[PDB]
Image 1 (cartoon, each protein chain N blue to C red):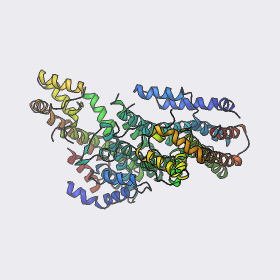
Image 2 (cartoon, rainbow over the protein chains, first blue to last red):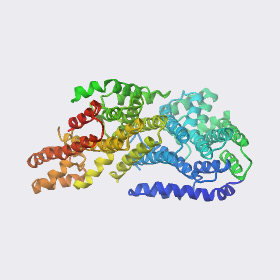
Image 3 (cartoon, chains in turn blue, green):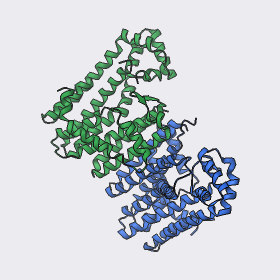
Image 4 (tube, rainbow over the protein chains, first blue to last red):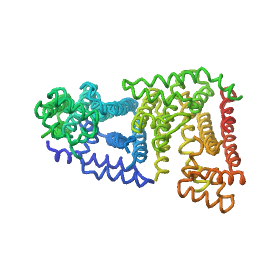
Length: 303
Length: 306
């Protein structure tokens, strides 16, 4: 089931999602208003809110509160991005990024509680705290060539996967699915979210490739080449991470990754996550909605 | 009842509030706990949680969960401080370097997010949809207000101090009441208390900003009650100076002439007066609750504030 079939199938619900977003983001501040337009007018994938609407329909949801979940999930993602834009002494602006970020987060929280489900609040509550924790952990890893791939995996699970997992699972809870099904949706997101981030990290080496390297941000493929390349390569990479600003070292780094398998090794691991995701969904009744969720897993790790 | 008294009465609970706060700084990510200890161990004030603890007892609460709510309320306030300092590019706060000047903006913003989300988790753990309901609204109202004054009247200014200050006080007392299962009548009592108290608290804070962090309001030409009065009643020269300073959003170096202008019109004392009328609305709102030492303290703080 290609992306086109998936879009048409989710067309109506995504319109509901966009309506939820516009009603929550309605002005006074041109800034907040034009942001609503920029989100609903986006020509992007918007895979997070879609998982939320698909997961609910997959377990037989008939009402339309799932659109509010999709919306609040997109808000959380948008806020984490705005906060991730904040620049340190290395200098929208910090104020705008911070304040608009706060507005969107808080509004997301209000939305969560409007659903009136304590369990949903329990799951989200933890998820967003875990996301904030992962962002900080990521801050600490900047310029640190020695983090374990265990730490790295905790980072991607925390900052990316967790939101997917909660998006899927909460829709399931709202639909009053069965414990078995709920878990199946939960895992699906965690695994898909994990795949999604692995693919993203490898694509950064392939807005411009080399950003992560340039920032001294250590990701799986870079860490892999460092642990498996030649001592000369490991040293160059270690230095690039410690000092940062090594964008000009992309090619030599690419040479080192090609040589020991880093990029394919990562893609491989991504594909494995996507398959654990699709497997998790096997507990759900085979329907077009479930087909769409599977189609997104494939699209996420494809090339 | 004065501070020394209101202090021992609520000594055991506020001690719990303290432990409840510090124990939440339990992340595997050390930077969070570090920055948390740095910002929460610098005195603070704890007037927001103290109101929470007192409001609960005042309505016969006998449990230990009001401690959990006072804790998260201080965490929420803590969070706004971490973000406020980053926004204001502030370097100092109560004697030492701000968390941002010391740890960097990103760390301050992110740990602040961790802190607010933990408070929300603490709120869900309490299991009351009404608390979550009242508290989430309050925090979003504050956040909205901050986005506004990013993108010159006596009435206009009274809306700003409400959104940014009074609203969290309001919720602090109301939610503490709700948790204890108070009466619709008592609830409205605590809520008004908090609103009015918080209102008086900000008015006082603004007058204290003119000598008695000192001086930032004038430095950024913030239109505070004190400054506005001086503009309205001073001489046209002083009136022009103040007005252009607010228009410039910068009144740095203008402290002496602005003060002169204030003492001639008696702007400060006047601020102290519309403030006094706020605190009198605060204890009046408590007339609805039962006569207990806890109530006497809530009235105490109102007087202490002004």
